[PDB]
Amino acid sequence: LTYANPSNMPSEDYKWGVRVANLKSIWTAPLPPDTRTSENMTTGTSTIDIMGLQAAYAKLHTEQERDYFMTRYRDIMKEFGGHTSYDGDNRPLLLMRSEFWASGYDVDGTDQSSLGQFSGRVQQTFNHKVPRFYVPEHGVIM
Amino acid sequence: TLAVTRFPPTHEMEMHYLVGKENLTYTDIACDPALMANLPPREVSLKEFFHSSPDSAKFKIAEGQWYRTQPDRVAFPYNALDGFPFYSALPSTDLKDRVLVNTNNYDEIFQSMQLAHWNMQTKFNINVYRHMPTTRDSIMTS
Image (cartoon, rainbow over all chains, first blue to last red):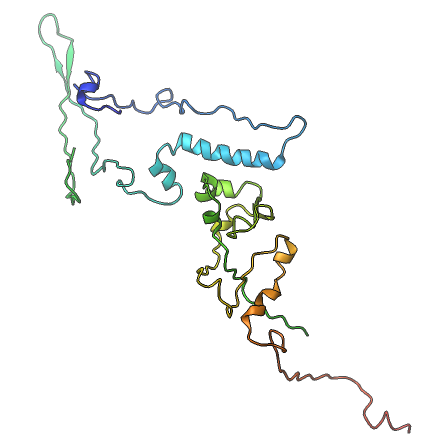
């Protein structure tokens, strides 16, 4: 999202915020669309290079990995056994994360017409704790 | 019983492969395990290792060999100095010759010499146990 100014983002993207991804299903987490279903190695007319073939496989491997898991530098790095500071790739630092399921209770209708009818009331008490944190430089915590 | 005196192959003009080969590709600089572990030996020239050497004198190296090793390094201030047991001259275009040591490139390291490059004075204390006649029983027709 290379939006320059909020006056550039879709009305509802900046009203309620941009759309997050659905929870992993089979159809809701397809393989990367640019995912190769085949790979050609230009061969000779009546011979193939047994050693070239080998190599062909080594390259496709490196490609496949980038496609499926290391689409991120910080990611192609980690698989090298190294690490990259959130300062190497200018990524906001995730300080804390809370997740929970919100619930509530049903309200029973009791008049002549809506007796046997209910309305679910979702009241969920939650709490989130961001442990003390040392701010290296000036910035915002979102 | 034979002797052989040698000096480590320190040339005054050997350059680090990666620093002598101009454009660095992903394969040369990343040291991707998958790659190094799976393509043919690389044919290189005395030119990717020595500062003036012909593009034409080739030899086959193992991919990523430049990452398993490190040449010795001799400052230019030296290559103009006789008295240092180093390799001044350039290699020998030819494989063989440029491996089996080039003795002559050590002539300049010594002062005067009618005792070659090296001389030795040793007392060979041998002891053989036989079943020999004897000194008197051989000269004793008897």
